[PDB]
Amino acid sequence: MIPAECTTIYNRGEHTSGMYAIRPSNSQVFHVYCDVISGSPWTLIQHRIDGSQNFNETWENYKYGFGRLDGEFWLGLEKIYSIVKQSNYVLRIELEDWKDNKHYIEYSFYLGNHETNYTLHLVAITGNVPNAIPENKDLVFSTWDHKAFNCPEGYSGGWWWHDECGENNLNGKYNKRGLSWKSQNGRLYSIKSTKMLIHPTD
Amino acid sequence: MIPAECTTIYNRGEHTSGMYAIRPSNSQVFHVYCDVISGSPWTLIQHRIDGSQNFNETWENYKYGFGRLDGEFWLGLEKIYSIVKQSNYVLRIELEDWKDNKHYIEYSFYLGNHETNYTLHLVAITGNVPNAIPENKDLVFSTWDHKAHFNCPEGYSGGWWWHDECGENNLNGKYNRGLSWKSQNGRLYSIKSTKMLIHPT
Amino acid sequence: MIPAECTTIYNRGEHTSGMYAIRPSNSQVFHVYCDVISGSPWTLIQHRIDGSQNFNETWENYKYGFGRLDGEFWLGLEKIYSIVKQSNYVLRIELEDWKDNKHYIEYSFYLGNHETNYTLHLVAITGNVPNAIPENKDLVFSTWDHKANCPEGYSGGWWWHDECGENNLNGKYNGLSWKSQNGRLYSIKSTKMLIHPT
Image (cartoon, rainbow over all chains, first blue to last red; front, side, top):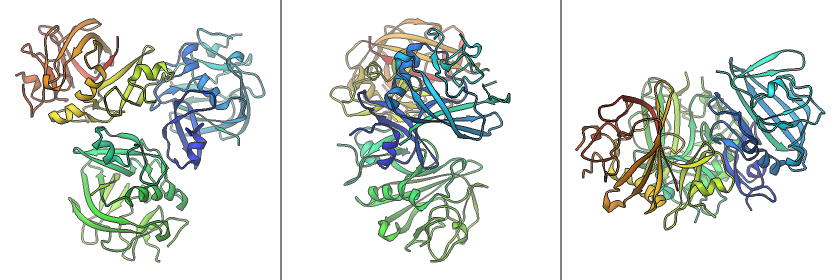
């Protein structure tokens, strides 16, 4: 009776973005920000705006969530996995630079449970910004107090990593200039604000 | 049990503005922004701040809503009708110009169902700025993909209620300076932010 | 089932700050802002950002609350009492200056009902700033339209004693003044008042 996630909230007639209660299978009720983009609903799992929220958090906090749902936040790996579980989901990354240009990229992904350290497997689909995250590789999540070779760009924040590493840490240190997104070719994008958004494939 | 509208929320002791769940009679639960103005509760049905949200939406999305309840949004004609068909409602239009002067006007009104293309019938009650919307006339809603009648120049873009008289009154129009409000006998008002608000009479 | 306060919300696994419904015993449902500070949940009862909200409100609005839960607001004395009742709670005051620094101070307190004019009785516990509010004294609430006086209290609703002093966080914004008597005057840009159980 309580919707499982944002797509079913949308299909039940809530077509506006905002904060909603959901309850995925085998889970407690918790609140999410549902973000409708061009008529399609997403669950917002990460949001960064100005660096005010410290993202160099513990493993426990990256697992259960931190921040403010009306501002900068991280939903929580346990909550994200409760949504995704064994399903193929779609991940959208939205970056805005300091010149206020908007870039997006979408991936098809699978996510493992806490026993796999929430291993992420991505394949890029579309976007107007080149990919910076290794594709078709098992990416292991790590925090400052919970290391999985340690990537130089993982020194701050919780992120998914492989030996190839890279400048791709959207949960990295917000320098007070923003964040960095270095694609495979070499072009590095200065990032002022980020969103990470998911929705089921079907 | 679940409050019917923002006035119900306020009367049950919740006097802060914010996003709340409501369930109008024989309707599904949905969320609204309750806006209390000078100690008086209102249900906010549209809000425009800086023109970041595109308002040149489909008929389908004007029926069911679009946008961000904590920002720029349109509640949706089906949901507006679900609220108002319960009783009789006052419509408050609030306009902010670029000098940050607040202007307002309040109307008595009734609203038809989808079978009438949500026809609006307005009577101006009070305000501090001239009314620009034809009164005591069936105003038919139209969008870019859903035309009822004659195409008004201020209605090329957006979902709005129109009559043969047209006029510069389309608060869901293209946001440039900003939006335009002008009565037939009055001067043009350049509008930076808008609100549309309803509560029972 | 509706949780009774922000501690239950957090313990149930919602560790993000924000607006949530709650329902203390013998009370209607109402919404609060749960603020998570260093992994500990607090109920935000007062919040001021930039003076956009007018805090020279009437007694009835100070009892039932006013403002925006995601912005500047006052939760309301009746709702604050619904949470605390005759329990001994903990109060935290958060003061942010204009130079971006943050100052805090924590109190043990108990609270009286409306026929008491919501008397506040507190004593400081910790804090990186001196206290400007009289400790271990019964401070009674008053608004511009409801007296029980201090010149710092001509604007806003606040708890007062004969000591007075610039400690009115609900006072007139320009920003706000926090000064212990014969001490440094802090000009405050933003304020937070938070409570949680012991």
